Amino acid sequence: MTADEKRSLQCYRRYIERSLNPVYVLGNMTDWLPDELRERIRKEEERGVSGAAALFLDAVLQLEARGWFRGMLDAMLAAGYTGLAEAIENWDFSKLEKLELHRQLLKRIEATMLEVDPVALIPYISTCLIDRECEEIQQISENRSKAAGITKLIECLCRSDKEHWPKSLQLALDTTGYYRASELWDKARSYQIELAQPAINGKNALICAPTGSGKTFVSILICEHHFQNMPAGRKAKVVFLATKVPVYEQQKNVFKHHFERQGYSVQGISGESVEKVIEDSDIIVVTPQILVNSFEDGTLTSLSIFTLMIFDECHNTTGNHPYNVLMTRYLEQKFNSASQLPQILGLTASVGVGNAKNIEETIEHICSLCSYLDIQAISTVRENIQELQRFMNKPEIDVRLVKRRIHNPFAAIISNLMSETEALMRTIDFGTQNYEHWIVVTQRKCRLLQLEDKEEESRICRALFICTEHLRKYNDALIISEDARIIDALSYLTEFFTNVKNGPYTELEQHLTAKFQEKEPELIALSKDETNENPKLEELVCILDDAYRYNPQTRTLLFAKTRALVSALKKCMEENPILNYIKPGVLDNRLLIATSVVQCNLVVLYEYSGNVTKMIQVGSKCILVTSKTEVVENEKCNRYKEEMMNKAVEKIQKWDEETFAKKIHNLQMKERVL
């Protein structure tokens, strides 16, 4: 067909003129396009590639020489447009159509990508782009500017005729570690045996052992003692309930991997028929809300299916949380039927202390929790503390209050710019990891929108991102300001706008940049003050210096608040006469500076709001440098509570079965009556 092919090609005009750049294909159209045209197409490309495409298509459609069509394909194939080649050759554009949503996305997220290093991206993105586009980006990136590059890269990705790309750009972003944009894109030890003992005896257990001691393993130990001793013709079944979905999957794969080989069936149900899955499996790793749904929903009305329910992070069993929903049903089947209930095993790092003030009030709280899970024993390492304490060395914490800036005008000036920006954002609590997270949430709310009038939709979303990316940059700059030097604050922002200018530079972006430029010369004048000194930083430098003298063979790990900081602090440690004998590293070196998560010997958290104990564990020594009375008098609280809990648990444990049973049973009867 000759004339079918032409009209067909007109019928998919848009799919072609929103990707092909004719210039890359005129080489091998030399037989069918005359000289003048070829040039004329090139000149139009300089004005608009979409245009050039349209024209080339315009000119080919009124062509008529032997076999231009095949020649067009054979040139497209050469050029690399293997997408288009297939899509016009089988007259199926479904694949290219699917892309128009990922294109529509990148353009909306663009502001996010400003500072992404396109040279670093290219090798992973390379199949998505054409020969010569890769070298154009490379050129713009080097010769002109780096933002200017990334802008031309995302320019090319949108014209990519490769269903394969969005997937590649995710992998691309992930490899080079742009983890914000990427995310936006889309046999046993003694103490272990001791922990297991009361569950192996068939008692309802609440293992309260610390994170790291390997509770999950103690559960698998309980699990295979459970199968091994199951009597009669009753077949055993197990559920491992896990709250958060990441924990769920680790566990699924762990239980899969351990037990499958021994002969069992280990499937894992989750948010992504329950009847069969539970019935065709011996072990079932699961999110609790599924059961709770499929119970009410009607799929299941009998909890006797199982012989053992293992609750991970079991302290959550209160009020509306699903475990409790599950358990209230369990507790009826005890009370109403007295048929055959599964064994309960709870797992947790801590059994809380509620709103307790006393050890008595703590006991009463722990006992309440136990009532909800129908616990008969609270299992903890006792005849083996020696060993546990070896395996993990819960390190002594030098809490150190440091003084802070008596006056911080830099903070004032930015804070107020954020306030003006937020203001303007609407029309379309600063300097905190809380804020940053707010931005991460707000940004997935724009990635969603997708609401109605798409032209006004894609102007409004574009706009939102730009604001939030600027709010982010300000937010960070405060955090540089507070924990590090004031110059490092401003420097950071300077580089930012310097790029903003080199990128797209939307009307809005210009406004925002301007609005900052209005305030810059103040900020510059503050950067100057040769008096300037962050008394926080000065104390860190002191602790560091003092650390390297009582033992000058000391490998220190320094945790800063943000990435912005790590780089900033490195400068400060580099430029200090006191730490002149020290060159710091990041992620030879006896001072590596990391951010919130290597061999060590003195760990130092430089500001950290939110508990330390758990951050350290994701050889002995640790210093928390805080400038807030809050933290100092707060971790002092957590210690008291931790000790109160333990005394209370030690106390309960020393009751006799009888007494504890009755307390738990009485507690349950109180609840039925209310």
Image (cartoon, rainbow, N blue to C red):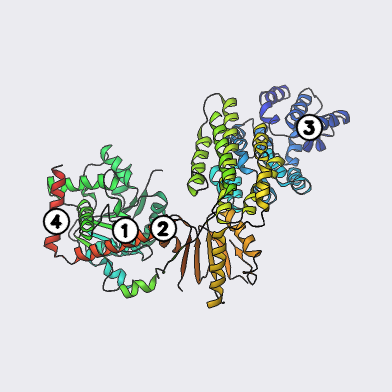
Q: How far apart are labels 4 and 1 at the CA level? A: 21 Å
On the picture, is 531 further left or further right than 363?
A: right
> Which residue type does callout 4 highlight?
Lys
- Please say if 611 is above or below 514: below
Where in the figure is residue 513, as x and y percent of width and height?
66, 38
Q: How far apart are labels 1 and 3 at the CA level? A: 65 Å
> Along the polypeptide, which appears first: circle 1 or circle 3?
3
> Along the polypeptide, which appears first: circle 3 or circle 2?
3
Where in the figure is residue 32, as x and y percent of width and height?
83, 30
Q: Which mark is residue 663?
A: 4
Q: Which residue is mark 1?
A: 348
Q: Is residue 515 visible?
A: yes
State the image quarter where residue 322 is shown: top left
The residue at the far right in this view is 35
> Along the polypeptide, which appears first: circle 4 or circle 2?
2
Q: Residue at x 77, y 47 (%)?
A: 139
